[PDB]
Length: 341
Length: 7
Image (cartoon, rainbow over all chains, first blue to last red; front, side):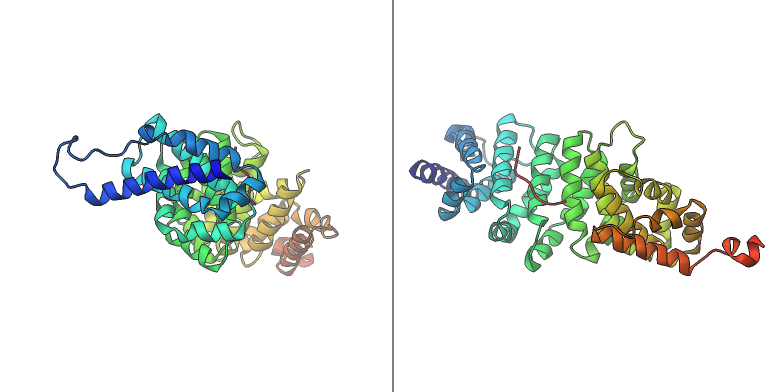
């Protein structure tokens, strides 16, 4: 499409102008000597707006991909972030939101485009830095990019997502988020990242207050949690629980936040995702700790798990049966025949 | 956590 080529050319030309400015701009001069390019003066927002709107259609995305659109839009977002930093300027915030939305659409279902954007490590660093923006709407857009990039990440993309500090940045972002729709995007990205490798799990667990926060996302008894929050927080917990099971300090954080009690409540949920997540978490936590095994026995876990072993869903069937096996292999003294007497 | 279009 020639309008699309026309728009991408405009964006590329602006970026080039910005790079040439960055390379010529000398320290300690007047504001007037070598003026910064202003995207308003180059009609950039309306260009990226049109491309964002077009990016919702798969045929328009195909045309964009043939003309290098992902790279052009990414370079634009990056250069604006580098030039202007964490600004509250409405034009800049809007530009960044539209660019990020386009990048979300262009990385959806497209393994090649995910790999390409991850390879742009300078852009990736700029994206991660925007999670500290005062705009929770920009936070949501950035988290949505990172969510898509972390879904079906290839070996190199996983390494890069880790390298640029996306896990710590997202977890720290989560602790301060007030808007549910922003939190949903942030937790969905973390759910993907938490599955990539053990080091990502450790990085989540290492953020001060993060485990208590995550257990907080599980509760029904909340004026802020929605179903989506419970699902995604529980998914993160399921993934990181393989590590937590081996760390007494982290188990203690879970204990003191009533995690086992809440997971047993989750077994009774009508939500398949919630039950699934709880079965995987209990699989892990029911191993190798007598204190937690006894609490589970006291609260009736054995029967609650037995009821789920015939599920058609692998995670429920396997996780419930495995947690049950762990409890049956480690019967507390007070439930042994010789002690009930 | 899956993937999604923008909004």
